[PDB]
Image (spheres, coloured by chain):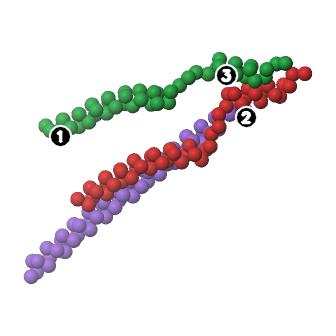
Chain colours: A green, B red, C purple
Amino acid sequence: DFDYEKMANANKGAMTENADENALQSDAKGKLDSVATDYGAAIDGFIGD
Amino acid sequence: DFDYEKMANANKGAMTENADENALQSDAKGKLDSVATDYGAAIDGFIGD
Amino acid sequence: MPVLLGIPLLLRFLGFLLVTLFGYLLTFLKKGFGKIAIAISLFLALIIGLNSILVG
C-alpha cells in the first residue's frame, strides 16, 4: 500500500529551497542604486566646474 | 505490482509548475514599453526647443 | 535530443527580449535622422530669408 503521493512530497522537500521574490529584488536594486548615485554625482560636478 | 508509470506521474506533478508563454511575454513588453515612451518623449522635446 | 521540462522556454524567451531591444534601437536611429532633416531645412531657410531683406 505504497503511498505514491507521500514519497513524491518527500522527494520535493529534499530537492527544493525557499525564496522570497520581493527580497531578492530589493537587494539587487540596493546595490545598483549606489553606483548610479556616484555616476550622477560625477556628471553633476563637472558641469559645475 | 508497482505501477511504475503512476509513481513517475506523481513525481512530475510535485516538482512542476504551470506557465503561459504568451502571458510572461506580454508583461515583460508592458514594462519595457513604458520606459521607451519616456526616452522618445525626451528626444522629441529637445528638437522642439 | 532529450532535455528538461523548462529549458525550451528559456531559449525562446532569450530571443524575445533581444528582438524587442533591437526594435527600440531602430526607432531611435530613425529619430536622429529626422534631426539632420530639421537642421538642414533651418539653415537653407535663414539664407533664403536674408536674401529677401538685402534685395529690398
Quadrant where the N terminus of chain B is found in the figure: top right
Residue B49 appearing in the image: yes
- The residue carrying mark 3 is A12
The residue beneath circle 1 is A47
Q: Locate residue A1: give its quadrant.
A: top right
Q: Secondary structure at mark 1?
A: loop
Q: CA distance from mark 2 to mark 1?
A: 58 Å
Residue identifier under label 2: C1
Residue visible at 78% across and 27% down in the picture: B8
State the separation of the CA atoms marked 3 and 1: 58 Å
Report the amino acid beneath label 3. Answer: Lys
Rounded to the nearest angstrom, the CA distance separating label 3 from label 2 is 26 Å
Three-letter code for the amino acid on which mark 2 is drawn? Met
Q: Is residue C18 visible in this depiction of the protein?
A: no
Sequence-first tag of 3 and 1: 3
The correct choice, above or below, for B19 with respect to A7 in the image is below
Find residue C55 and report its horizontal and vertical position in percent. 10, 81
Name the mark nearer the viewer: 3 or 2. Answer: 3
Q: Amino acid at mark 1?
A: Ile
* Other-residue count near label 3 (Cα within 10 Å), few / some / many at <14 / 14–19 / ≥20: some
For residue A21, above or below residue A15: below
* Occupied quadrant, residue A31: top left
Relative horizontal placement of residue C53, taking residue B41 as reference (left or right): left
Q: Is residue C34 above or below residue A49?
A: below
State whether discs 2 and 1 lie on one chain: no
Tell me what residue is drawn at x 75 percent, y 27 percent.
B10
Label 2 sits on a secondary structure element that is loop
Marked residue chain, label 3: A
Question: Of A48 and B18, which appears nearest the observer?
Answer: B18
